[PDB]
Length: 212
Ligand SMILES: Nc1ncnc2c1ncn2[C@@H]1O[C@H](CSCC[C@H](N)C(=O)O)[C@@H](O)[C@H]1O
Image (cartoon, rainbow, N blue to C red; front, side, top):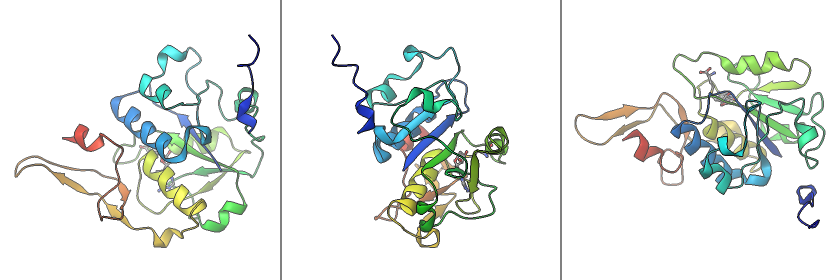
């Protein structure tokens, strides 16, 4: 049969450079949330190890239609005909150490938004800089405020700024929220989270259950 080889993909893009070994439960929950929020057609998981095959991708992510590749930023265009050439200046790296905060007018300046697929540590190990130094002529950096976010929070904030055109200063965050389940067990999450319409921090589905 010849009809299922169709390049239907042709009919803002988010790129996560996977920088973890394998897929921990937390990574799977975060990536799942990202897929649900930006859509499988608008997300690329890149830079997976060269030995990566479909059996190495978690079934929770494949079920959501994850588009993934072992190519890095410079090779992605070979793999997806639908991805506009990643070109110098039009690719934004979201970087906690950028000088300039992302603003809605940056929607006119960039076509691709790149994030480290990193489970951040505290203190940060500044691994996102690796990305900036790996592609010195491709990427232009933008910040999302002065506090570390998880990958799914950073993508959610970027979508609020770029698609919904909301200024960074207008986004309601909660910094380092505590989740207490009894008078003796509590967990403070050392990241900045977006607040939902109900005043609660937005976490990936199942994250709360995992923390407890
Ligand atoms: N304040 C901020 N500004 C811009 N991007 C951010 C951000 N906080 C998180 N991100 C995005 O979310 C990703 C995961 S968090 C950063 C990992 C941390 N630097 C460490 O090495 O431990 C980053 O790679 C970045 O792309």
